[PDB]
Image (cartoon, rainbow, N blue to C red; front, side, top):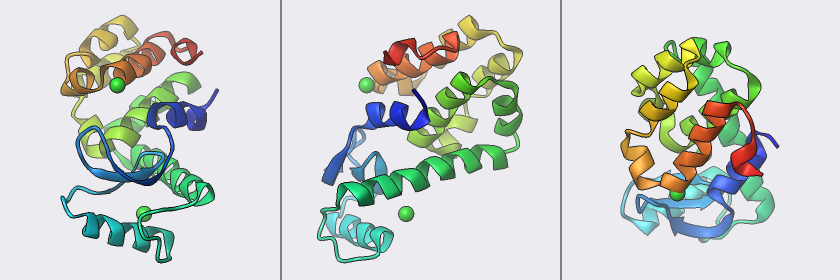
Length: 162
Ligand SMILES: [Cl-]
Ligand SMILES: [Cl-]
């Protein structure tokens, strides 16, 4: 198991534009197209991203290419962020993966606002941080996924995904 398999499980794969759990237009492996309510706007964003006239449908290969870019962007977003980097650097590989999952879903923004959890994480107070992360809109909205990620963080193992 790794970050790619892990997120492909959390996000699934859809080749037609769809609405995510917040009702935003998405496609592929969790790639958000836009926060606007226009499907047109979504279709245009999809075309600009793939570089062709898609008409709201992409291939598997195109999905994967987006996903690759997006995982990459999540990692670099972390490394570039001054509060996150040192947290991420302090951890082992499994837990880093939990962190990337969070950033991928919620954006650099959303995740940097878990300050308190980040401190605990940096101190390696796993059970505590686990309790803290669950007091969040994130856990309340997408609880099954949130649990998977939080277990990973807590245990440092891939059990929740096996
Ligand atoms: Cl893009
Ligand atoms: Cl969920």
